[PDB]
Image (cartoon, rainbow, N blue to C red):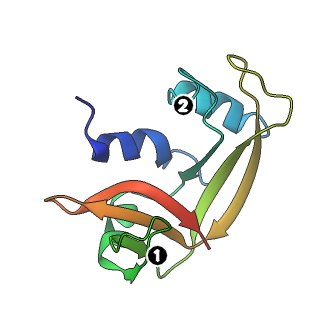
Amino acid sequence: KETAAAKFERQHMDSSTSASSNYCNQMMKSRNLTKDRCKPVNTFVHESLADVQAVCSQKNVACKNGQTNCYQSYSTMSITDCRETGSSKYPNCAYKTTQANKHIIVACEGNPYVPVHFDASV
C-alpha cells in the first residue's frame, strides 16, 4: 500500500526546482493527481525533504478539520499553488501555476513523526 508519508512526498514535494506557466499542467499529471479526476487544488513545496519534515517540530496550530496535529513553518518556503482552470475538463486537466513564498501548514503523524497532509499556506 502507498503510505501516507510517501503519498505526501508524491503530492507535495518538488525540491528539484527553486520556484514555468506549464509547471502545474505537467506536474499534476506526472504526480498522478489527474488519474481518477482533476484534483482541484494542490501545492508543491520547493524546499529539501529534511526542511519540510522539520516543520513537524515547529509551530503547532489547529488543522482546518479541527484536529490538533498541524504545524506551521517558522520560515517562509518556496511553493507553487496549482488551481484547476474554469475550462479544465477531465481527462485534459488544466491548471494555473502560481509561485509564492509563504509559511506552510502540514499535518504530521506516525513514528517517525512526518508530514502526511498539506493543510494550508499563510
Residue lying farthest to the top in this orientation: 91
Image spot of residue 57 (x, y percent): 29, 77
Residue visible at 43% across and 64% down? 106
Camera-side residue of 78 and 72:
72
Give the quadrant of residue 77: bottom right
* Other residues around mark 1 within 10 Å, as few (<14) / some (14–19) / many (≥20): many
Image spot of residue 119 (x, y percent): 50, 61
Q: Amino acid at mark 1?
A: Ser
Q: In this picture, is 62 found above or below 118? A: below
Q: Tell me if 78 is positioned left or right of 113 in this view.
A: right
- Would you name the residue on which mark 2 appears? 33
Q: In this picture, is 121 found above or below 12? A: below
Residue visible at 76% across and 22% down? 89
Residue visible at 48% across and 49% down? 15
Dot 2 lies on which element? loop
Marks 2 and 1 in Cβ contact (< 8 Å): no
